[PDB]
Image: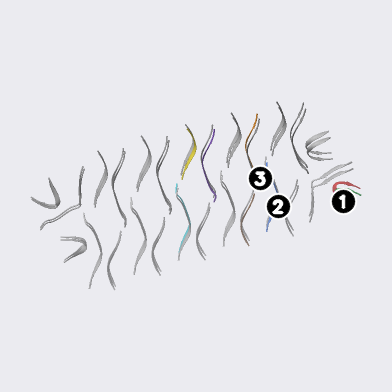
Chain colours: C blue, G green, H red, J orange, M brown, Q purple, S yellow, X cyan
Amino acid sequence: GMLGGVVIA
Amino acid sequence: GMLGGVVIA
Amino acid sequence: GPLGMLGGVVIA
Amino acid sequence: GPLGMLGGVVIA
Amino acid sequence: GPLGMLGGVVIA
Amino acid sequence: GPLGMLGGVVIA
Amino acid sequence: GMLGGVVIA
Amino acid sequence: GMLGGVVIA
Amino acid sequence: GPLGMLGGVVIA
Amino acid sequence: GPLGMLGGVVIA
Amino acid sequence: GMLGGVVIA
Amino acid sequence: GMLGGVVIA
Amino acid sequence: GMLGGVVIA
Amino acid sequence: GPLGMLGGVVIA
Amino acid sequence: GMLGGVVIA
Amino acid sequence: GPLGMLGGVVIA
Amino acid sequence: GPLGMLGGVVIA
Amino acid sequence: GPLGMLGGVVIA
Amino acid sequence: GMLGGVVIA
Amino acid sequence: GMLGGVVIA
Amino acid sequence: GMLGGVVIA
Amino acid sequence: GMLGGVVIA
Amino acid sequence: GPLGMLGGVVIA
Amino acid sequence: GPLGMLGGVVIA
Amino acid sequence: GPLGMLGGVVIA
Amino acid sequence: GPLGMLGGVVIA
Amino acid sequence: GMLGGVVIA
Amino acid sequence: GMLGGVVIA
Amino acid sequence: GMLGGVVIA
Amino acid sequence: GMLGGVVIA
Amino acid sequence: GPLGMLGGVVIA
Amino acid sequence: GPLGMLGGVVIA
Amino acid sequence: GPLGMLGGVVIA
Amino acid sequence: GPLGMLGGVVIA
Amino acid sequence: GMLGGVVIA
Amino acid sequence: GMLGGVVIA
Amino acid sequence: GMLGGVVIA
Amino acid sequence: GMLGGVVIA
Amino acid sequence: GPLGMLGGVVIA
Amino acid sequence: GPLGMLGGVVIA
Amino acid sequence: GMLGGVVIA
Amino acid sequence: GMLGGVVIA
Amino acid sequence: GPLGMLGGVVIA
Amino acid sequence: GPLGMLGGVVIA
Amino acid sequence: GMLGGVVIA
Amino acid sequence: GMLGGVVIA
Amino acid sequence: GPLGMLGGVVIA
Amino acid sequence: GPLGMLGGVVIA
Amino acid sequence: GMLGGVVIA
Amino acid sequence: GMLGGVVIA
Amino acid sequence: GMLGGVVIA
Amino acid sequence: GMLGGVVIA
């Protein structure tokens, strides 16, 4: 649907 | 659908 | 220094 | 110094 | 043994 | 033995 | 399938 | 399939 | 984002 | 983004 | 004597 | 004596 | 509809 | 100095 | 619809 | 100095 | 918006 | 918007 | 005599 | 005599 | 619909 | 629809 | 000095 | 000095 | 509007 | 609007 | 001596 | 001596 | 109906 | 109807 | 000097 | 000097 | 309207 | 309207 | 000596 | 000596 | 009816 | 009816 | 001199 | 001299 | 007779 | 007779 | 008899 | 009799 | 000498 | 000498 | 990956 | 990858 | 051996 | 041996 | 004496 | 004496 964002550190 | 962005560090 | 991370923004 | 990261912005 | 490093994976 | 590192996985 | 730090098949 | 830091087939 | 303020450091 | 302010550093 | 720094915000 | 720096924001 | 604005920092 | 943030204004 | 503006920093 | 951010204004 | 007043700073 | 006033700084 | 500054408003 | 500055408004 | 004015500061 | 004015500063 | 703000006047 | 802001006047 | 009166300022 | 009166400023 | 100012209204 | 100013209204 | 005047100061 | 004047100062 | 403000007069 | 403001006069 | 009278001012 | 009178000012 | 002023109405 | 002013109405 | 005069001052 | 005069000053 | 104000006179 | 203000006179 | 705001006879 | 704002006879 | 008016007298 | 008016007299 | 409203010598 | 509104010598 | 910070080491 | 920070090392 | 902020062996 | 902020062996 | 290192972060 | 190193970050 809608995905804001992904942060993998 | 819609993906804002991805940050992989 | 300061470390900032933002994945993404969806404006719909 | 300061480290900033932003993936992307979608304006729809 | 082997030394393998993977930062990350995002699958769309 | 092997040394493997995975930062993360997000599956969409 | 399989995923992880170390995956021995 | 398979994924990870080290993948031994 | 993060906001960091440091005055100074004296290494004597 | 991140905002870092450092006055100064004296290494004596 | 010794002064590291001054920040005026 | 010694002064590192001054920031005027 | 109507959106004024967006500030991202 | 002073920091001011306004997102937006809608006058319908 | 109507969007005023977007600031990205 | 002073920092001011405004996203947008809509006058319908 | 924000209103800031500083008279002065003497670093002696 | 933001309004900032600083008189002066003396670094002596 | 050391005076930093004066603001008159 | 050291005067940083004067603001008149 | 009567609006005098708007001040944004 | 009557609007006098808008000031943005 | 003096600071004055008036939004608006509707004389109907 | 003096600062004055008026949005608008509607004389209907 | 606002009315502000200041006679004078002496910085000796 | 706003009315501001200042006689004078002396910086000796 | 020293006089700042005079407002006569 | 020293006089800043005079406003006569 | 009737209105003499308006002063906006 | 009737309006004498408006002064915007 | 003297300050006089009068809105208006309606002579019907 | 003197300051006089009059909106208006309606002589009906 | 308002009536104002001032004789004189001596600044010495 | 408003009536204002001032005789004189001596700045010495 | 010193006379500020005189008002005779 | 010094006379500011005179107002005779 | 009758109105003699009006003085606005 | 009748109105003599009006003085606006 | 004298300061006289007469509004009006109605003689029917 | 005298300051006289007469609005008006109605003689029917 | 005499009629006025100020009547000096 | 006499009629006015100031009537001096 | 006579009609005399004196507003005032100041003797310095 | 006579009608005399004197507004005022100042003697310095 | 003599002064006043009415002075009759 | 003599002064006033009416002075009759 | 890992975030490692080492100040220093003195080997004497 | 890893983020490593080493200040310094003194070997004597 | 090994030395560092991050030491992966 | 090994030394560091992060030591993975 | 001896100082190994300093990290400002 | 001796100083190894400094990191300003």
Residue Q7 image offset from top left, x and y in percent: 50, 41
Task: Indicate which label's residue lies in the foreground, 3 or 1.
Answer: 3
Q7 falls in the magenta region: no
Closer to us: M3 or G9: G9
Would you call the spot at circle 2 few (<14 residues within 10 Å), some (14-19), or many (20 or more)? many
Q: Are both tags, 3 and 1, on one chain?
A: no
Q: Mark 2 belongs to which amino acid?
A: Gly
**Magenta part of the protein: which range?**
G1-4
* Label 1 close to label 2 by CB (< 8 Å): no
Please name the residue shown 66% across and 45% down the image.
J2
Does residue X12 show up? no
Seen in the picture, residue H8 relative to Q10 is either above or below; the reply is: below
- Disc 1 marks which residue? H2
Question: Disc 2 on helix, strand or loop?
Answer: strand
Q: CA separation, marks 1 and 2? A: 28 Å
Seen in the picture, residue Q1 relative to Q7 is either above or below; the reply is: below
Does residue Q8 show up? yes
Image quarter where the C terminus of chain J lies is top right
Seen in the picture, residue Q12 relative to G3 is either above or below; the reply is: above
Q: Mark 1 belongs to which amino acid?
A: Met
Closer to us: C11 or H2: H2
Give the quadrant of residue Q12.
top right
Q: Is residue C9 left or right of residue S3?
A: right
- Disc 2 marks which residue? C8
